[PDB]
Length: 97
Length: 105
Length: 48
Length: 241
Ligand SMILES: *[C@@H]1O[C@H](CO)[C@@H](O[C@@H]2O[C@H](CO)[C@@H](O)[C@H](O)[C@H]2NC(C)=O)[C@H](O)[C@H]1NC(C)=O
Image (tube, rainbow over all chains, first blue to last red; front, side, top):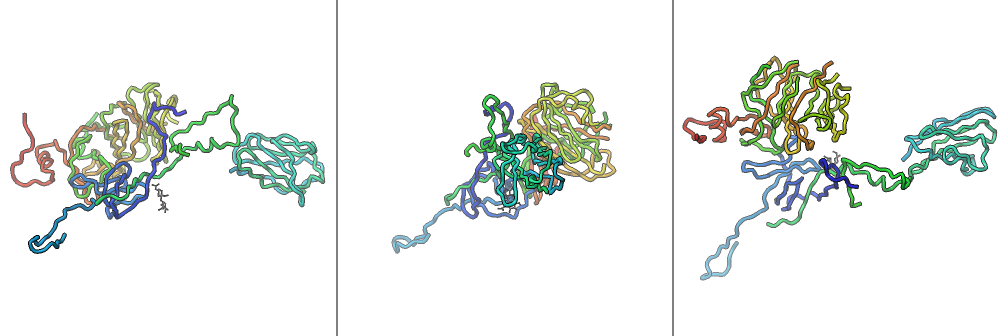
Protein backbone atom coordinates (compact mmCIF):
# COMPACT_ATOMS: atom_id res chain seq x y z
CA UNK A 1 0.00 0.00 0.00
CA UNK A 2 1.55 3.27 -1.18
CA UNK A 3 0.39 5.91 1.29
CA UNK A 4 -0.27 8.85 -1.01
CA UNK A 5 1.39 12.24 -0.66
CA UNK A 6 0.18 14.24 2.34
CA UNK A 7 3.68 15.32 3.40
CA UNK A 8 6.76 15.63 1.13
CA UNK A 9 7.69 12.17 -0.11
CA UNK A 10 10.84 10.32 0.95
CA UNK A 11 10.68 6.98 -0.94
CA UNK A 12 11.12 6.36 -4.66
CA UNK A 13 13.35 4.63 -7.16
CA UNK A 14 17.03 5.03 -7.94
CA UNK A 15 18.22 7.23 -10.79
CA UNK A 16 20.53 5.51 -13.26
CA UNK A 17 23.58 7.00 -14.94
CA UNK A 18 26.09 6.28 -17.70
CA UNK A 19 29.88 6.28 -17.87
CA UNK A 20 31.95 9.46 -18.03
CA UNK A 21 33.35 9.87 -21.54
CA UNK A 22 35.85 12.69 -22.01
CA UNK A 23 37.44 14.50 -24.99
CA UNK A 24 34.38 13.88 -27.24
CA UNK A 25 31.24 15.99 -28.04
CA UNK A 26 28.44 14.48 -25.88
CA UNK A 27 24.94 15.61 -24.76
CA UNK A 28 25.18 15.64 -20.94
CA UNK A 29 23.01 15.70 -17.77
CA UNK A 30 24.85 16.24 -14.45
CA UNK A 31 22.28 16.29 -11.59
CA UNK A 32 19.88 18.30 -13.79
CA UNK A 33 22.12 20.76 -15.72
CA UNK A 34 21.65 19.81 -19.40
CA UNK A 35 23.79 20.87 -22.41
CA UNK A 36 26.07 19.67 -25.27
CA UNK A 37 29.87 20.12 -25.28
CA UNK A 38 33.31 18.51 -24.91
CA UNK A 39 34.19 17.59 -21.30
CA UNK A 40 37.85 17.70 -20.17
CA UNK A 41 39.70 17.64 -16.81
CA UNK A 42 40.12 21.01 -15.04
CA UNK A 43 42.57 22.77 -12.70
CA UNK A 44 39.78 24.91 -11.14
CA UNK A 45 39.39 24.65 -7.32
CA UNK A 46 35.68 25.05 -6.39
CA UNK A 47 34.97 25.50 -2.65
CA UNK A 48 33.39 22.30 -1.13
CA UNK A 49 29.71 23.39 -1.38
CA UNK A 50 29.97 24.66 -5.02
CA UNK A 51 28.56 22.41 -7.79
CA UNK A 52 28.89 24.25 -11.15
CA UNK A 53 30.80 27.29 -12.52
CA UNK A 54 29.32 30.24 -14.47
CA UNK A 55 31.57 32.80 -16.29
CA UNK A 56 31.38 36.64 -16.85
CA UNK A 57 28.55 36.27 -19.43
CA UNK A 58 26.60 33.81 -17.18
CA UNK A 59 27.32 30.67 -19.29
CA UNK A 60 28.08 27.36 -17.47
CA UNK A 61 31.75 26.43 -18.10
CA UNK A 62 32.38 23.80 -15.39
CA UNK A 63 30.51 20.93 -13.59
CA UNK A 64 31.61 18.66 -10.69
CA UNK A 65 30.93 14.99 -11.55
CA UNK A 66 28.39 13.93 -8.88
CA UNK A 67 29.78 10.41 -8.11
CA UNK A 68 33.55 11.14 -8.10
CA UNK A 69 34.03 14.77 -7.05
CA UNK A 70 36.27 15.84 -9.98
CA UNK A 71 35.96 19.35 -11.52
CA UNK A 72 35.49 19.12 -15.31
CA UNK A 73 35.36 21.86 -17.99
CA UNK A 74 32.72 22.31 -20.74
CA UNK A 75 34.13 23.70 -24.05
CA UNK A 76 31.77 24.20 -27.03
CA UNK A 77 31.74 21.66 -29.92
CA UNK A 78 33.70 22.96 -32.96
CA UNK A 79 31.78 25.20 -35.36
CA UNK A 80 32.81 27.59 -38.09
CA UNK A 81 32.63 28.52 -41.74
CA UNK A 82 33.87 26.84 -44.93
CA UNK A 83 35.50 28.85 -47.70
CA UNK A 84 36.51 27.84 -51.22
CA UNK A 85 39.64 29.34 -52.80
CA UNK A 86 39.61 29.32 -56.59
CA UNK A 87 41.85 30.81 -59.30
CA UNK A 88 38.78 31.30 -61.46
CA UNK A 89 37.23 28.81 -63.88
CA UNK A 90 38.76 30.78 -66.77
CA UNK A 91 42.14 29.22 -65.89
CA UNK A 92 41.57 26.00 -63.92
CA UNK A 93 38.99 23.92 -62.07
CA UNK A 94 41.24 23.02 -59.12
CA UNK A 95 40.23 24.59 -55.81
CA UNK A 96 41.34 24.64 -52.18
CA UNK A 97 39.24 24.63 -49.01
CA UNK B 1 23.38 -15.15 9.59
CA UNK B 2 22.81 -16.21 13.19
CA UNK B 3 25.81 -16.38 15.53
CA UNK B 4 25.10 -18.66 18.47
CA UNK B 5 27.62 -19.03 21.30
CA UNK B 6 27.70 -22.20 23.42
CA UNK B 7 29.14 -20.72 26.61
CA UNK B 8 29.73 -24.01 28.53
CA UNK B 9 32.66 -26.13 27.42
CA UNK B 10 34.40 -29.39 28.39
CA UNK B 11 32.86 -30.18 31.78
CA UNK B 12 33.63 -32.81 34.42
CA UNK B 13 31.08 -34.19 36.88
CA UNK B 14 30.38 -37.43 38.75
CA UNK B 15 27.71 -39.92 37.66
CA UNK B 16 24.23 -38.98 38.84
CA UNK B 17 24.52 -35.21 39.21
CA UNK B 18 22.70 -32.17 37.88
CA UNK B 19 24.27 -30.65 34.76
CA UNK B 20 23.13 -27.50 32.94
CA UNK B 21 24.41 -26.10 29.65
CA UNK B 22 23.46 -22.84 27.95
CA UNK B 23 23.46 -21.81 24.29
CA UNK B 24 23.20 -18.03 23.91
CA UNK B 25 21.88 -16.48 20.70
CA UNK B 26 22.94 -13.34 18.84
CA UNK B 27 19.32 -12.18 18.70
CA UNK B 28 16.09 -13.59 20.07
CA UNK B 29 14.57 -16.54 18.22
CA UNK B 30 11.11 -17.81 19.13
CA UNK B 31 12.08 -21.20 20.60
CA UNK B 32 13.31 -22.51 17.23
CA UNK B 33 15.92 -24.81 18.75
CA UNK B 34 17.33 -28.30 18.22
CA UNK B 35 19.71 -30.27 20.45
CA UNK B 36 21.82 -32.98 18.80
CA UNK B 37 23.70 -35.90 20.35
CA UNK B 38 27.15 -36.81 19.04
CA UNK B 39 29.55 -39.63 19.91
CA UNK B 40 33.07 -40.28 18.60
CA UNK B 41 32.95 -42.60 15.61
CA UNK B 42 29.15 -42.29 15.42
CA UNK B 43 26.89 -40.17 13.25
CA UNK B 44 25.01 -37.29 14.92
CA UNK B 45 21.73 -38.32 16.54
CA UNK B 46 18.69 -36.08 16.89
CA UNK B 47 17.99 -35.51 20.58
CA UNK B 48 15.58 -32.60 21.15
CA UNK B 49 13.39 -30.57 18.80
CA UNK B 50 11.43 -27.33 19.28
CA UNK B 51 13.30 -26.03 22.34
CA UNK B 52 11.58 -27.81 25.25
CA UNK B 53 10.20 -30.95 23.63
CA UNK B 54 11.50 -34.49 24.16
CA UNK B 55 11.85 -36.87 21.23
CA UNK B 56 10.73 -40.49 21.33
CA UNK B 57 13.38 -42.96 22.45
CA UNK B 58 15.30 -40.53 24.67
CA UNK B 59 15.77 -40.80 28.47
CA UNK B 60 13.62 -38.42 30.51
CA UNK B 61 16.65 -36.93 32.29
CA UNK B 62 17.19 -34.54 29.37
CA UNK B 63 15.04 -31.42 29.48
CA UNK B 64 15.00 -28.11 27.64
CA UNK B 65 14.15 -24.57 28.69
CA UNK B 66 14.60 -20.96 27.66
CA UNK B 67 12.68 -18.45 25.55
CA UNK B 68 14.18 -16.07 23.01
CA UNK B 69 17.87 -16.17 23.92
CA UNK B 70 18.41 -18.07 27.22
CA UNK B 71 18.10 -21.59 25.79
CA UNK B 72 19.38 -24.25 28.19
CA UNK B 73 19.60 -28.04 28.36
CA UNK B 74 19.48 -29.66 31.80
CA UNK B 75 20.10 -33.28 32.78
CA UNK B 76 19.03 -34.19 36.31
CA UNK B 77 21.05 -37.41 36.69
CA UNK B 78 24.34 -37.95 34.89
CA UNK B 79 25.12 -41.37 33.44
CA UNK B 80 28.31 -43.05 32.18
CA UNK B 81 26.68 -43.36 28.74
CA UNK B 82 25.88 -39.62 28.83
CA UNK B 83 29.56 -38.69 28.39
CA UNK B 84 29.40 -37.37 24.82
CA UNK B 85 29.06 -34.19 22.75
CA UNK B 86 26.04 -31.89 22.42
CA UNK B 87 25.36 -29.68 19.39
CA UNK B 88 23.12 -26.63 19.15
CA UNK B 89 20.97 -25.81 16.15
CA UNK B 90 18.61 -23.01 15.18
CA UNK B 91 16.16 -22.76 12.29
CA UNK B 92 14.66 -19.28 12.55
CA UNK B 93 16.24 -17.90 9.39
CA UNK B 94 17.14 -20.12 6.46
CA UNK B 95 20.88 -19.96 7.14
CA UNK B 96 20.89 -22.88 9.58
CA UNK B 97 23.99 -22.52 11.77
CA UNK B 98 25.00 -25.03 14.44
CA UNK B 99 26.67 -24.33 17.78
CA UNK B 100 30.24 -24.53 19.02
CA UNK B 101 29.51 -27.62 21.10
CA UNK B 102 30.30 -28.84 24.60
CA UNK B 103 32.27 -31.82 25.89
CA UNK B 104 31.33 -34.12 28.77
CA UNK B 105 33.38 -36.64 30.74
CA UNK C 1 30.43 19.01 -35.18
CA UNK C 2 27.56 16.79 -34.09
CA UNK C 3 27.33 15.02 -30.72
CA UNK C 4 28.08 11.29 -30.80
CA UNK C 5 27.24 9.77 -27.40
CA UNK C 6 24.90 10.82 -24.58
CA UNK C 7 25.71 10.60 -20.88
CA UNK C 8 23.89 11.27 -17.61
CA UNK C 9 25.43 11.34 -14.14
CA UNK C 10 23.73 11.12 -10.75
CA UNK C 11 24.91 10.56 -7.17
CA UNK C 12 25.64 7.12 -5.77
CA UNK C 13 22.63 4.87 -5.16
CA UNK C 14 22.72 4.40 -1.39
CA UNK C 15 20.22 3.27 1.30
CA UNK C 16 18.09 0.81 -0.73
CA UNK C 17 14.65 -0.03 0.86
CA UNK C 18 14.75 -3.60 2.37
CA UNK C 19 11.58 -5.15 0.85
CA UNK C 20 13.69 -8.10 -0.39
CA UNK C 21 13.96 -9.46 3.20
CA UNK C 22 10.13 -9.36 3.68
CA UNK C 23 9.62 -11.17 0.30
CA UNK C 24 11.99 -14.05 1.24
CA UNK C 25 11.06 -15.20 4.78
CA UNK C 26 11.51 -18.67 6.39
CA UNK C 27 8.48 -17.88 8.64
CA UNK C 28 5.26 -16.38 7.16
CA UNK C 29 2.50 -14.80 9.32
CA UNK C 30 -0.99 -16.43 9.46
CA UNK C 31 -3.70 -14.75 7.30
CA UNK C 32 -5.81 -13.55 10.29
CA UNK C 33 -2.70 -12.10 12.04
CA UNK C 34 -1.38 -10.06 9.05
CA UNK C 35 1.80 -8.07 9.90
CA UNK C 36 2.49 -4.50 8.62
CA UNK C 37 6.09 -3.36 7.87
CA UNK C 38 6.67 0.39 7.25
CA UNK C 39 9.18 1.17 4.47
CA UNK C 40 10.23 4.85 4.81
CA UNK C 41 13.04 7.31 3.77
CA UNK C 42 14.91 4.92 1.37
CA UNK C 43 15.59 4.23 -2.36
CA UNK C 44 13.07 1.63 -3.62
CA UNK C 45 13.76 -0.39 -6.81
CA UNK C 46 10.46 -1.93 -7.96
CA UNK C 47 12.09 -3.34 -11.11
CA UNK C 48 13.49 -6.30 -9.16
CA UNK D 1 16.35 46.78 24.67
CA UNK D 2 19.54 48.42 23.43
CA UNK D 3 20.56 48.67 19.78
CA UNK D 4 23.94 48.11 18.14
CA UNK D 5 25.15 48.99 14.65
CA UNK D 6 26.11 46.14 12.32
CA UNK D 7 29.32 46.97 10.42
CA UNK D 8 28.96 45.23 7.05
CA UNK D 9 27.96 41.83 8.42
CA UNK D 10 25.37 39.31 7.32
CA UNK D 11 26.44 38.31 3.80
CA UNK D 12 26.19 34.74 2.55
CA UNK D 13 26.70 32.74 -0.61
CA UNK D 14 23.34 32.98 -2.44
CA UNK D 15 23.94 29.99 -4.74
CA UNK D 16 26.24 27.04 -5.45
CA UNK D 17 27.87 28.73 -8.46
CA UNK D 18 31.64 29.17 -8.67
CA UNK D 19 32.74 32.56 -10.02
CA UNK D 20 36.40 33.56 -10.32
CA UNK D 21 37.49 37.22 -10.43
CA UNK D 22 34.00 38.58 -11.11
CA UNK D 23 31.97 41.50 -9.76
CA UNK D 24 28.53 39.89 -9.64
CA UNK D 25 25.28 41.74 -8.97
CA UNK D 26 22.53 39.90 -7.09
CA UNK D 27 19.11 40.75 -5.67
CA UNK D 28 18.02 38.72 -2.64
CA UNK D 29 17.31 38.80 1.10
CA UNK D 30 20.25 40.48 2.84
CA UNK D 31 20.92 42.47 6.00
CA UNK D 32 21.42 46.16 5.13
CA UNK D 33 24.83 47.62 5.91
CA UNK D 34 25.09 49.93 8.93
CA UNK D 35 21.76 48.95 10.47
CA UNK D 36 20.53 48.81 14.06
CA UNK D 37 20.01 45.35 15.55
CA UNK D 38 18.54 44.64 18.98
CA UNK D 39 20.96 43.53 21.70
CA UNK D 40 19.81 40.93 24.23
CA UNK D 41 21.63 39.86 27.38
CA UNK D 42 20.86 37.03 29.80
CA UNK D 43 14.61 35.73 25.65
CA UNK D 44 10.94 35.90 24.64
CA UNK D 45 9.33 34.81 21.38
CA UNK D 46 10.24 36.84 18.30
CA UNK D 47 8.87 37.18 14.76
CA UNK D 48 10.49 35.57 11.71
CA UNK D 49 10.43 37.82 8.63
CA UNK D 50 11.91 36.10 5.55
CA UNK D 51 14.75 34.89 7.76
CA UNK D 52 16.90 36.22 10.56
CA UNK D 53 20.58 36.84 11.34
CA UNK D 54 21.66 35.66 14.79
CA UNK D 55 25.05 36.51 16.30
CA UNK D 56 26.41 35.08 19.56
CA UNK D 57 29.73 35.99 21.16
CA UNK D 58 29.64 32.99 23.50
CA UNK D 59 31.27 29.58 23.22
CA UNK D 60 30.89 27.28 26.21
CA UNK D 61 27.39 25.76 26.29
CA UNK D 62 24.65 28.36 26.78
CA UNK D 63 23.27 28.74 23.23
CA UNK D 64 22.59 25.29 21.76
CA UNK D 65 19.14 25.41 20.19
CA UNK D 66 16.20 27.17 18.53
CA UNK D 67 12.45 26.69 18.11
CA UNK D 68 10.28 27.78 15.18
CA UNK D 69 6.57 27.96 14.46
CA UNK D 70 3.65 30.19 13.52
CA UNK D 71 0.85 29.66 16.08
CA UNK D 72 2.39 26.93 18.22
CA UNK D 73 -0.29 24.61 19.64
CA UNK D 74 -0.83 20.86 19.95
CA UNK D 75 -1.70 20.89 16.22
CA UNK D 76 0.93 23.03 14.45
CA UNK D 77 4.45 21.82 13.76
CA UNK D 78 7.59 23.12 15.46
CA UNK D 79 11.25 23.02 14.41
CA UNK D 80 13.74 21.72 16.99
CA UNK D 81 17.42 22.39 16.33
CA UNK D 82 18.74 21.64 19.82
CA UNK D 83 22.46 20.88 19.81
CA UNK D 84 24.15 18.19 21.89
CA UNK D 85 27.86 17.87 22.66
CA UNK D 86 28.21 15.54 19.66
CA UNK D 87 24.96 15.70 17.64
CA UNK D 88 22.06 17.91 16.58
CA UNK D 89 18.49 16.74 16.04
CA UNK D 90 16.06 18.26 13.54
CA UNK D 91 12.59 17.55 14.95
CA UNK D 92 9.68 19.22 13.16
CA UNK D 93 6.92 17.96 15.43
CA UNK D 94 3.24 18.80 16.03
CA UNK D 95 3.13 19.85 19.69
CA UNK D 96 2.86 22.76 22.10
CA UNK D 97 5.17 23.55 25.01
CA UNK D 98 4.77 25.36 28.31
CA UNK D 99 5.74 29.00 28.78
CA UNK D 100 9.43 29.77 29.37
CA UNK D 101 11.10 26.63 27.97
CA UNK D 102 14.81 25.93 28.26
CA UNK D 103 17.42 23.21 28.73
CA UNK D 104 18.00 22.09 32.32
CA UNK D 105 15.93 15.81 29.45
CA UNK D 106 14.45 19.17 28.46
CA UNK D 107 11.96 21.46 30.18
CA UNK D 108 9.72 21.87 27.13
CA UNK D 109 9.68 18.19 26.12
CA UNK D 110 7.53 17.30 29.14
CA UNK D 111 4.74 16.95 26.55
CA UNK D 112 6.65 17.88 23.36
CA UNK D 113 6.79 14.46 21.70
CA UNK D 114 3.43 14.56 19.93
CA UNK D 115 2.77 13.22 16.41
CA UNK D 116 6.13 14.19 14.97
CA UNK D 117 7.11 13.96 11.31
CA UNK D 118 10.78 14.35 10.37
CA UNK D 119 14.12 13.56 12.02
CA UNK D 120 17.72 14.40 11.13
CA UNK D 121 21.15 14.17 12.77
CA UNK D 122 24.09 15.76 10.94
CA UNK D 123 26.10 18.41 12.81
CA UNK D 124 28.27 17.34 15.80
CA UNK D 125 33.64 34.71 23.77
CA UNK D 126 36.79 33.56 21.98
CA UNK D 127 34.82 32.63 18.85
CA UNK D 128 31.88 34.61 17.50
CA UNK D 129 29.15 32.46 15.95
CA UNK D 130 27.06 33.88 13.10
CA UNK D 131 23.95 32.18 11.70
CA UNK D 132 21.30 33.03 9.12
CA UNK D 133 17.96 31.20 9.01
CA UNK D 134 15.83 31.32 5.86
CA UNK D 135 12.45 29.73 5.14
CA UNK D 136 11.07 29.87 1.61
CA UNK D 137 9.25 27.64 -0.92
CA UNK D 138 8.89 24.82 1.59
CA UNK D 139 12.62 24.79 2.38
CA UNK D 140 14.66 25.76 5.43
CA UNK D 141 18.23 26.95 4.86
CA UNK D 142 20.98 27.45 7.44
CA UNK D 143 24.08 29.58 6.92
CA UNK D 144 26.83 29.63 9.54
CA UNK D 145 30.29 31.02 10.19
CA UNK D 146 32.85 30.92 13.00
CA UNK D 147 35.29 33.78 13.60
CA UNK D 148 38.05 34.30 16.21
CA UNK D 149 37.53 37.77 17.69
CA UNK D 150 38.50 39.54 20.91
CA UNK D 151 37.71 42.68 22.93
CA UNK D 152 34.58 43.62 20.97
CA UNK D 153 31.23 44.57 22.51
CA UNK D 154 29.53 45.41 19.22
CA UNK D 155 30.11 43.31 16.13
CA UNK D 156 33.69 43.25 14.79
CA UNK D 157 35.01 45.34 11.92
CA UNK D 158 35.69 43.23 8.85
CA UNK D 159 34.13 41.10 6.15
CA UNK D 160 33.15 37.43 6.27
CA UNK D 161 30.82 35.29 4.17
CA UNK D 162 28.42 32.69 5.59
CA UNK D 163 28.73 29.29 3.93
CA UNK D 164 25.57 27.14 3.72
CA UNK D 165 25.00 24.32 6.20
CA UNK D 166 21.81 22.42 5.33
CA UNK D 167 18.77 22.65 3.07
CA UNK D 168 15.84 20.78 4.57
CA UNK D 169 12.34 20.13 3.10
CA UNK D 170 10.20 20.82 6.17
CA UNK D 171 7.36 22.04 3.95
CA UNK D 172 5.63 24.00 6.72
CA UNK D 173 5.14 27.62 7.78
CA UNK D 174 7.24 29.49 10.34
CA UNK D 175 6.38 32.90 11.81
CA UNK D 176 7.61 32.91 15.43
CA UNK D 177 11.16 32.20 16.55
CA UNK D 178 12.70 31.64 19.97
CA UNK D 179 15.93 30.39 21.52
CA UNK D 180 16.46 27.60 24.06
CA UNK D 181 18.95 28.83 26.64
CA UNK D 182 20.69 26.07 28.61
CA UNK D 183 19.52 27.44 31.96
CA UNK D 184 21.24 25.32 34.60
CA UNK D 185 25.47 35.72 27.72
CA UNK D 186 24.64 38.25 25.00
CA UNK D 187 23.31 37.87 21.47
CA UNK D 188 22.19 40.00 18.53
CA UNK D 189 19.23 39.61 16.17
CA UNK D 190 18.72 41.28 12.80
CA UNK D 191 16.09 41.12 10.07
CA UNK D 192 16.67 40.47 6.37
CA UNK D 193 15.25 42.68 3.63
CA UNK D 194 15.07 42.44 -0.17
CA UNK D 195 18.21 44.27 -1.30
CA UNK D 196 20.59 44.43 -4.25
CA UNK D 197 24.26 43.66 -3.61
CA UNK D 198 27.49 43.78 -5.63
CA UNK D 199 29.57 40.79 -4.55
CA UNK D 200 33.28 40.56 -5.37
CA UNK D 201 34.34 36.98 -6.00
CA UNK D 202 38.13 36.65 -6.01
CA UNK D 203 40.31 34.17 -7.90
CA UNK D 204 39.49 31.19 -5.66
CA UNK D 205 35.75 31.91 -5.66
CA UNK D 206 35.55 33.44 -2.17
CA UNK D 207 33.50 36.59 -1.65
CA UNK D 208 35.85 39.35 -0.49
CA UNK D 209 33.77 42.56 -0.55
CA UNK D 210 30.21 43.74 -1.08
CA UNK D 211 28.40 47.00 -1.79
CA UNK D 212 24.90 47.98 -0.68
CA UNK D 213 23.19 49.22 -3.86
CA UNK D 214 20.96 51.62 -1.85
CA UNK D 215 23.13 52.95 1.00
CA UNK D 216 24.25 56.33 -0.36
CA UNK D 217 24.71 57.98 -3.77
CA UNK D 218 28.32 56.79 -4.03
CA UNK D 219 27.25 53.18 -3.52
CA UNK D 220 24.61 53.68 -6.20
CA UNK D 221 27.29 54.97 -8.57
CA UNK D 222 29.53 51.97 -7.86
CA UNK D 223 26.56 49.63 -8.31
CA UNK D 224 25.65 51.23 -11.65
CA UNK D 225 29.20 51.18 -13.03
CA UNK D 226 29.69 47.62 -11.69
CA UNK D 227 33.09 48.53 -10.26
CA UNK D 228 34.42 49.35 -6.80
CA UNK D 229 36.47 52.34 -8.03
CA UNK D 230 35.07 55.30 -9.95
CA UNK D 231 37.04 58.20 -11.40
CA UNK D 232 36.33 61.91 -11.53
CA UNK D 233 33.18 62.93 -13.35
CA UNK D 234 29.39 62.99 -13.39
CA UNK D 235 27.44 59.73 -13.66
CA UNK D 236 23.69 59.37 -14.09
CA UNK D 237 22.37 56.72 -11.70
CA UNK D 238 18.60 56.77 -11.14
CA UNK D 239 15.35 58.55 -12.00
CA UNK D 240 13.51 60.99 -9.73
CA UNK D 241 9.72 61.13 -9.86
C1 LIG E 1 30.48 6.96 -5.12
O1 LIG E 1 30.79 5.60 -5.45
C2 LIG E 1 32.11 5.42 -5.99
C3 LIG E 1 32.22 3.97 -6.38
O2 LIG E 1 32.05 3.11 -5.26
C4 LIG E 1 33.14 5.85 -4.96
O3 LIG E 1 34.44 5.74 -5.54
C5 LIG E 1 35.32 5.03 -4.65
O4 LIG E 1 35.65 5.81 -3.49
C6 LIG E 1 36.53 5.15 -2.57
C7 LIG E 1 36.68 6.06 -1.38
O5 LIG E 1 37.58 7.13 -1.65
C8 LIG E 1 37.85 4.83 -3.26
O6 LIG E 1 38.70 4.13 -2.36
C9 LIG E 1 37.60 4.00 -4.51
O7 LIG E 1 38.82 3.80 -5.21
C10 LIG E 1 36.59 4.69 -5.42
N1 LIG E 1 36.29 3.86 -6.58
C11 LIG E 1 36.72 4.14 -7.81
C12 LIG E 1 36.32 3.18 -8.88
O8 LIG E 1 37.41 5.13 -8.05
C13 LIG E 1 32.89 7.29 -4.52
O9 LIG E 1 33.77 7.64 -3.47
C14 LIG E 1 31.45 7.46 -4.05
N2 LIG E 1 31.19 8.85 -3.72
C15 LIG E 1 30.26 9.23 -2.84
C16 LIG E 1 30.14 10.71 -2.62
O10 LIG E 1 29.56 8.43 -2.25
